[PDB]
Image: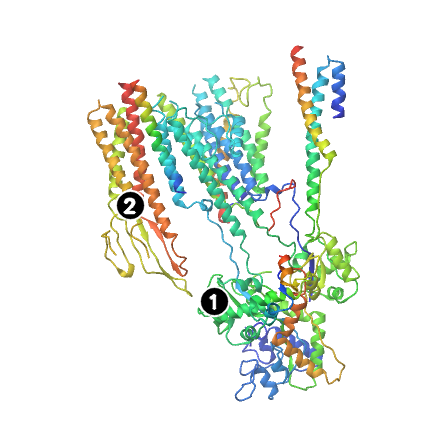
Amino acid sequence: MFIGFILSNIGHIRPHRTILAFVSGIFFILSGLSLVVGLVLYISSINDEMLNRTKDAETYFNYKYGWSFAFAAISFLLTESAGVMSVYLFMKRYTAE
Amino acid sequence: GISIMIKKPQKSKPGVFSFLDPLAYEIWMCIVFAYIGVSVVLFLVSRFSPYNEFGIFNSLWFSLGAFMQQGCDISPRSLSGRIVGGVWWFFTLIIISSYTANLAAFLTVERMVSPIESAEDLSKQTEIAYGTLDSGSTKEFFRRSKIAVFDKMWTYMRSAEPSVFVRTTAEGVARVRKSKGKYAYLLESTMNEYIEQRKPCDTMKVGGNLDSKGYGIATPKGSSLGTPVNLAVLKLSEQGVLDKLKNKWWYDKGECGAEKTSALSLSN
Amino acid sequence: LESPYVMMKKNHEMLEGNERYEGYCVDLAAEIAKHCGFKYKLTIVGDGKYGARDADTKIWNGMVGELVYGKADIAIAPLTITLVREEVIDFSKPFMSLGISIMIKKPQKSKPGVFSFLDPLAYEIWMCIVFAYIGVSVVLFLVSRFSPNEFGIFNSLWFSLGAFMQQGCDISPRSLSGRIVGGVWWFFTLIIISSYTANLAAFLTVERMVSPIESAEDLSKQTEIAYGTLDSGSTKEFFRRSKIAVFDKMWTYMRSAEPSVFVRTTAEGVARVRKSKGKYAYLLESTMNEYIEQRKPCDTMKVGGNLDSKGYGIATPKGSSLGTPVNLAVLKLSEQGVLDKLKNKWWYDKGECGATSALSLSNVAGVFYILVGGLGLAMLVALIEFCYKSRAEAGRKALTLLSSVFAVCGLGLLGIAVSTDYWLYLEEGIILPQNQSTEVKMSLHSGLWRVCFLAGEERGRCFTIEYVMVNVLKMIRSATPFPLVSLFFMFIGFILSNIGHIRPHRTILAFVSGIFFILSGLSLVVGLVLYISSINDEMLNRTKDAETYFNYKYGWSFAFAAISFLLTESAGVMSVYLFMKRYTAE
Amino acid sequence: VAGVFYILVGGLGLAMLVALIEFCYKSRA
Amino acid sequence: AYGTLDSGSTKEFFRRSKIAVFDKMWTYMRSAEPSVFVRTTAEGVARV
Amino acid sequence: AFTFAAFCYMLTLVLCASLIFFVIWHIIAFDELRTDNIERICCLLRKLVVPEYSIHGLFCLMFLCAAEWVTLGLNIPLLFYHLWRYFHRPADGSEVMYDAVSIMNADILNYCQKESWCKLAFYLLSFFYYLYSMVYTLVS
């Protein structure tokens, strides 16, 4: 996402360079695709541990996601939405070229 | 008698390819090669005696579309082509109805099994490490044993690092409950069947007794108790009293008694 | 003389002395002799018994009575340590431990059928689906190539085979006449496939809810598998005296059940395990149970831990000078492992047998055979299309003769079937235990109108309706009119066909007759459904009737009625294809 | 599953009568 | 959990009992120590 | 009985049965070039070349995954025979695959003729090889 923001801003302050724009656009989705496996392997590992509760009657366990988990998940929405519209920038600039 | 103590097997740990369990791995190979088998035959039949649209690339996409229950934009327009599509549509109907109906049998009926059920089975494993006590008649049994299997179990733990022998029975029961099913401790079978009936209710006895020995009521050599005690043990045993006093302390005064359907987690 | 303990060698008589015998206890004898210092000399006990006090005469017998009363010094033999023997003889510590255990038949795994995927729906459904699929496609041909094109009889079969297999349809009806036929076939294929998947999940679950016998508490619960003990010995007397809750339930069972579960020989009780197909669970002692397992063709198996704890022992008379060195020889041999070696040699190393929760390719195997048989069929058709297209490069007549013959043979096959009484074969009777033979007591070969017995109490006499006076009589009489209407519409359809043929101008007599050929077939489906529904409804009231059996079987008139469905539809569409050409040529 | 065969054949016969109505209406008018 | 009054014929029934079902009930209530032996009708209705 | 190995023999049986029709088609196609149409025979042979190699290329992957080491070992030297045959005329004018570069290929006409009998040799050998081998596996 940071590399994708680098080539986006210099694609914006230098609007001639269309190839810097669209390739940056790919990094916005590859952030989000990595973030899904980020969330899956996180949530997989939490569920794998709780399955070894060793049946523990009269005991209890409880897990609960917080607000940084929500900010990480909302970030998935933004990087994809900024992803497609960075490509829709390349859709118009290559057309207007 | 000497017997094997393992931690009681839990539910699972869902693998990465755990969803492939309702159909055996020979079916998932016979699905992949039938899909390529149908796509080749559909290609051949479409080219010869034409109508066109079905190259090899579209015949891989028609027969993938038909397997995933989502039939595509193009369909064959010939009697020789529709037989290929027709019998492949009946194949995916039965296979996906067999995947669903077997997966619903898994989740309904939990049936947990054991890794090892013998000392012969333990002899060939090398992922579960054994253990005895560092000085006692259990260790000395394997040392002098010569028959077939107990030699092999000795030569392992004689050699195996990090020195699987423990030096207290409470330590060995601890290393069963801590090593997550990688440790099988070799106890006398009166001590397995007692700890199996104690909270945490965490361990289990597997297999049969490896040797045979007994308990005894001792007296001095010449005492006048020696003869009536001997005929009392045989009198108590035949009435059923000695079998009843075991069930009272082992299997009645023990905490461990004798389907919840957890929702599918993301790990499955 | 008992195996494996002491047996005669093959090579005896030409042998004499101690060297006639082989087995466990003649190997154990040569070990205690080496330790104690004997010069031993085996005999065999004269009687052939172990030992018991004859309560009338108070006289012992067997190996206990041979050394209480004289002529023996030692008794190296399976002499169980009991109290009534211990009062007169002098046992060693046990050289072998044992107990009562459970002998059942080795489960004998079952290769599933080739077409066992067709089991969740009974074959009367798989028959009527194929009858429905031809039934819909001809109607969908009719109702769409009559109103205002692309729905010929070749494409209408591919719509309906598209819609049944849940795959999408390339074309779709664009008429309210056609969109009802598409609508009711989409609801038919939704209930059927939800009934296949659901009943298959009821097969595979209930198969997974079957736990085998691996305990006494497991075997205590059931009543389908018979228990069994020797009728004279400590095994029967164990459960009598027993005051443990599990063995209370076992003795309460075996006290009252009268196919006899009390055998009076070891050898016969092993047979009733072998020839009763997992319906017998003979309670043997754990040393004969582990031996018979490792023997002659490996049909039996030991399940569960031992019920009690017993032991064997040597037996010196009462006060002999080899009563203490024999006790210290057993406890020396038990620790060196010699007593565990001599058991493995005779039970296992001289043995005669030997030492997944997923669908495999044996369950769904017919779908691969239909797939390969389908791809093989298609290239056979593809070679026909290749040759016939080159022959095409290098009408009224053909359709006429095919429609007429399929009409009159449709008359013939149904006309025989509506009269001749060979529809159903009912065969109820009784079954017999201990041989499993299937005694017939009542056969029948009735039909639609006139019932006929064949061997029921050897009645060779037929019957009829007669409002006369176990089965019922008014079960076929429900779906009586629909085979009769199958005559009416087909005969009327043949009337207007023939005068349409001998007067070829009258096209309106032809096509309307064509409708009656399908309406015969549509009435014949409900003819077959309500017939087969009524037969299945009666058999569900079997009133659970254990040890009884019922059996039903369709005949040849049922086949002629069902083949008539194929003909009336095929003559149906081609009578319309006559109207397709004549109205065109007009 | 017997009523599904009854709804089917009842659904087929109901659909022929539509085409019997539809043809009669069309050809006249 | 089962439960009987700790003083009365209801408790003394299972003690003397030699029927297989009530054997298992008395064997249970003999040894379980959150206390299943109430000593009033009114309190035992509450624990239901 | 029915295992993954046995299905691979059933599937290559039904695919080799088209390979023996691939030969009966082109041996009459080669021979009518002798008795006559050299352009239209040359293009009709072209569109049936890439089916032959790639179907046989499937077979090598099939018995490799089937762990039939023997039956793999048979047609790997046929695959070399096929793979070596790929690059011999690489100045082709973008045409699909073999026997069209010099389009009136008539000079040798035997290096194509020895193949047409070599194709019929192993493929008729295969159809009776894979027929016995599947029946071997099923009853075993």
Occupied quadrant, residue B190: bottom right
Is F61 positioned to the left or the right of C518 in the image? right
Identify whether F93 is placed above or below C191: above
Q: Position of residue B44 (x, y in %)?
A: 48, 29
Q: Residue furthest top?
A: A97
Occupied quadrant, residue A73: top right
Q: Chain of mark 2?
A: C
Q: Chain of mark 1?
A: C
Question: At numbered mark 1, what does the secondary structure look like: helix, strand or loop?
Answer: helix
Going from N to C along the chain, the mark reached first, 1 or 2, is 1
**Residue at (64, 54) in percent of width and height:** B114
Q: Can I make out residue C96 in this image?
A: no
* Residue type, mark 1 in image: Arg
Q: Nearer the viewer, mark 1 or mark 2?
A: 2
Q: Which mark is residue C557?
A: 2
Colouring scheme, one of rainbow, by chain, secondary structure, one colour: rainbow
Residue underneath mark 1: C272
Question: At numbered mark 2, what does the secondary structure look like: helix, strand or loop?
Answer: helix
Front one among B135 and E41: E41
* Residue type, mark 2 in image: Ser
Query: Which quadrant does the C terminus of chain C fall into?
Result: top left
